[PDB]
Amino acid sequence: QEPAGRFTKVAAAVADSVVTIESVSDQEGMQGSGVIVDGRGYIVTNNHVISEAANNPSQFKTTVVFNDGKEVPANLVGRDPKTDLAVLKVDNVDNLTVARLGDSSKVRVGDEVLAVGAPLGLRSTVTQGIVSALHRPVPLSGEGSDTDTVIDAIQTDASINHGNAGGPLIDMDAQVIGINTAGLGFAIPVNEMKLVANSLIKDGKIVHPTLGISTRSVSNAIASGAQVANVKAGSPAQKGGILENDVIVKVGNRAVADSDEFVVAVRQLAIGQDAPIEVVREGRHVTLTVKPDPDSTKL
């Protein structure tokens, strides 16, 4: 309608892009949300939405449910537990309404957002709020024996819940600016999603940089830095001159407030090139140089 509200118009516009994701076994049953990102049938969700199914593919049958009601099977193209993203493939489906993606770098504090979940899902919700913060590191608990991670989130005061998760964060132009993830809500920004989706589409898996160090945050609520707890034998850090008890304050061009920012900062680096790591050892400001390894447990 034309007497229709601002958020009602936007929610209706994106509805056909948003998808239900169900994984059924003879015992358990999971349900989340997803967004259609490619006309060939590529869908983005959270890793945690599909986590249990991917861990036990044998016994789990994952299906996609469209806004029109149609139910097709879906295959895992790939997943990244480190960024809580996953891509799913759907075969030979006609006239998918592909979501228009936005630019998460042009997002500002105060912008009005809709956290949109699957229209036909069971717990399913559409929530509204503003962007509370940009580039906010959030630790996420990887359930079902997945590794715990930190993501660089868009913080929103829109409520993100079971009925929302894996669905898009949508701005006022009906553009996807994030994937809903997790007392306020958090989203993975769409620019990161694009990079991760493309690495997953291309070769099934994604490789992240590592430095070889573990950290502890130095101050309680102030940005004092990330203290080095251990430097592992032969690590990029050790070869670079990171000592234990150093306080890391900048990795690349990104500043480092604490442990959480440290994790998201390292992920921003490229595996090949040399990168500066600013540090405060026993008093003085020294800028070490590190070349990050891949994080593979494989050649």
Image (spheres, grey):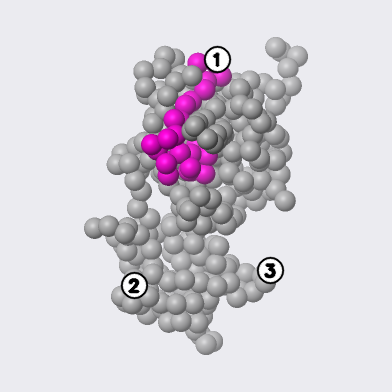
Q: Which mark is residue 68?
A: 1
Q: Which mark is residue 297?
A: none
Residue 289 shows up from this direction? no
Task: State the CA–CA distance, disc 3 to disc 2.
Answer: 30 Å
Tag 1: amino acid: Asp
Residue at 47% x, 26% y: name it: 63
- Decide: is 26 above or below 281: above
- Identify residue for label 3: 221
123 or 201, which is in the foreground? 123
Question: Of helix, strand and loop, which one carries label 3?
Answer: loop
Task: State the CA–CA distance, disc 3 to disc 1.
Answer: 48 Å
Disc 2 and disc 1 in contact, CB within 8 angstroms: no
Looking at marks 3 and 2 on the same chain, the residue that comes earlier in the sequence is marked by 3
Q: Which quadrant would residue 260 be assigned to in this image?
A: bottom right
Tag 3: amino acid: Ala
Asked if residue 51 lies in the magenta stretch, the reply is yes
